[PDB]
Length: 146
Length: 146
Image 1 (tube, rainbow over the protein chains, first blue to last red):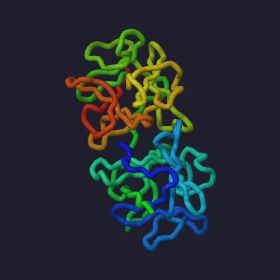
Image 2 (tube, each protein chain N blue to C red):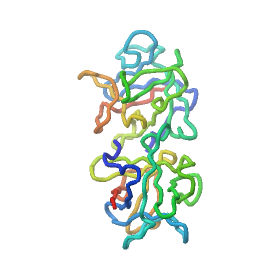
Image 3 (cartoon, rainbow over the protein chains, first blue to last red):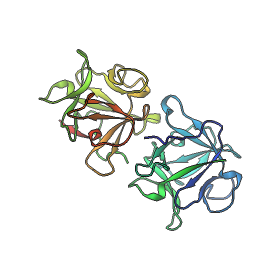
Image 4 (cartoon, each protein chain N blue to C red):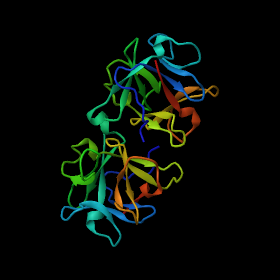
């Protein structure tokens, strides 16, 4: 089932991993442009959601507040997770927020295009990325409303 | 994760529930036009999949062999599950086959449009339909290749 509390259009938030406590960022200078961060708030950690309609109903594009790029998550090229201009021009810009079956307070950030979920862990390279496979706790996220 | 063995285009199959053992049918005479059946093989239990591309990548339309209609699963009108002409002209004609997390040999027939899954049970009206909510064993299906 979809996560029951998905931010409305225009609502700003951070995406913080339940267990690592790190947040996603999306920036335009210095690789990796999309990764996780353990530290203080910076504006490149701020997102809003473009609410999908039509063929994108129940999917969302994750849009950077300061730079306007949207996230992508793919298996078709490297890097597998990154950002891009265009307000969701590509299929792999669209995400579903799926409630965890055993922890009602968290969700996975799921790509239908790549059948993958974003993860964040404090050890084990690569510490952030996407993943197609079994369910692990490092795949669980919160919306942190600002 | 998506069910690892999804029939290729042109491959005919029945959809049989793991536990009830009943099969889905899709017919053009006599309500309910889409429901489940406990009995012998009839052609209205035969389907192929239209493989989605683009915005429909990893989704499929479930197309009747004898009558060509595709299934729909929705929460916008009654009946919530039915069939329709058009080879997938509507968003609620598109389905994902999602492997069960605890039984690798079965999957749910999932609607992104309605955040619902098809179910079949031997008692409890309605015995067949779609459902948005917790995971139950009556939501688990097999492809039965013919």
